[PDB]
Length: 8
Length: 8
Length: 227
Length: 226
Image 1 (tube, rainbow over the protein chains, first blue to last red):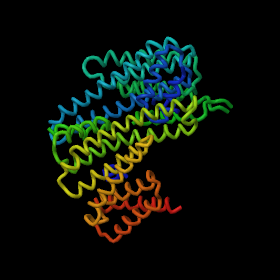
Image 2 (image 1 turned 135 degrees about the vertical axis):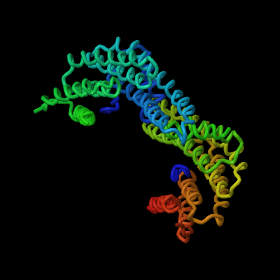
Image 3 (image 1 turned 90 degrees about the vertical axis):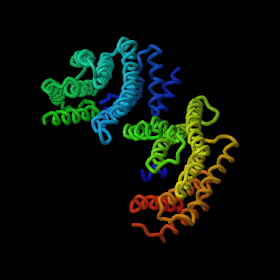
Image 4 (image 1 turned 180 degrees about the horizontal axis):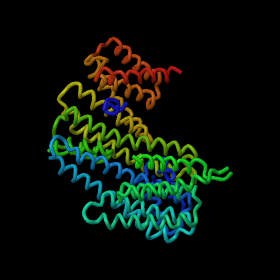
């Protein structure tokens, strides 16, 4: 949601 | 796999 | 040839189990008694294929009870739960066919038979889970039939440590509980197998960890149903 | 409408069916609306998991090809399967691109969002480069460069280093310079640049959600230090 939303 | 090949 | 196996071994490695299973679904379709290696690969493949959907359906199903705000999403939740159910059944039947058509009637090794029959039970039990309506009672007994045939063969030409026999046990022990909803029968069977598998404490031949790994599941199941 | 597929996708996440999830977001974009934060994120979460699966699938198959090369009778089936995934990812990448280049950046109304979707371009083209065989890569690499740099202009001197979307850009553009352009010197430059500027920022989910991004930069900086 925070790491995976922005793809690392 | 132990349970992976036995599907547990 | 075994080019598919190789594809599967890659599909396994690629976690592309959908392909993997299709590969082995074809190897089966080739109409040969799959090597315990191949066997394992087919299972591995379909294990995740049916596993993907069960764990999908499971969350949707529970969310079906936990509908966004009111019970208005019920329609969507269900509709989609059914979308999964459709797929799951396809995969199940697909596996079941393989079992009826190739696996069971080809499996020469007694051990192998147990395995596939267990699959039968397993995959039939995966239907029962989803089998709402009036189907369950029959389908649950169709899973049972399958598990029992396996049990019969296991308690015959399989030592109590054999991970498959224990694999069956656990898979069949979970059936009586989760499915038939009869802890009485479930708990006993589990105990029986584990209890019987204990005497063989291998003071110097066993099935190492694989077998012990199940015992833990078995007892960890037993202790859950204990409560 | 759009919501008629915002609940379904939310459930597809819940049910780990990102292929469905993605397909719901596609229609939500095809609706013709500047995506929300909820709805945008989902699209990412959805497609990131779809591409991610392929990318991580490709990486292992490519890695398996490191047993027999372009001309062999044992690692010839890998390349052919890797190529199948190459295709799959491409289709999925192009799909996200079609969504992004058609009506993902032009429809986006906000400024902070511009960065984001462009960061996807810098992401998704980079994915293409990795798999982009032949001489075609060269251009596809520029695609990601033109993109990830373009988003860097909108995120640079526009949002505080504290911003996780500005820092997420840093991460991905740096890993683009390193992993694709194989220009560690330039990668570490961008990283330091972002991290440095990001230090001189002050924010009271920016507390942690914007702290992990930084921790990766530092980790990468460290990795590329040795």
